[PDB]
Length: 208
View 1: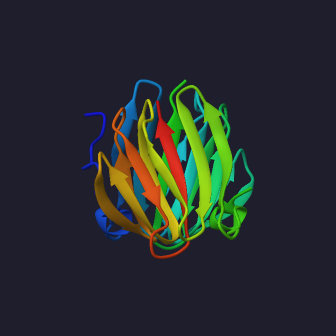
View 2 (view 1 turned 90 degrees about the vertical axis):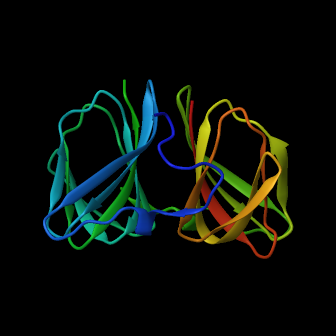
């Protein structure tokens, strides 16, 4: 209802959501009163159009290539890219091939996300992208051997591994999330993470 996929488990969104010719497929995966996370798969040459939205929209592309026209301005989007679209803007999104997107929305130029944080030896580097009362998005790099101790968040977090692989724990239970996979760390339950076997990067989307 609020989390529509299994928690504390690695999931490959590329496999979870697919479209055949001429289809647009969508799925809500987290839903709260004033923010949500959805997935889209657009078949080649299909489009989604959005009228002047009451809140901001953010997109992370995990497959394919496309074009976004925001009030008549072509931005290109590709696998690995992140894009913010501010409130009160008409836009359309066109798929040039099979375009898959995570859409993060508040209800009321594209760049490569992994490249925004560097690895640093023995360190965790964190860069906050959005920080709002219903939505927090942060990108992090972990050098092998670095970890976060168990902690809780007041919302459900979706983590997606952008590079390498990470070892996550939810309420003491371990699971590996590999590059291209995601997992939900549920609200009010302790979780932790460790760069156990190699360096990794992740995007964290917390909906509160």
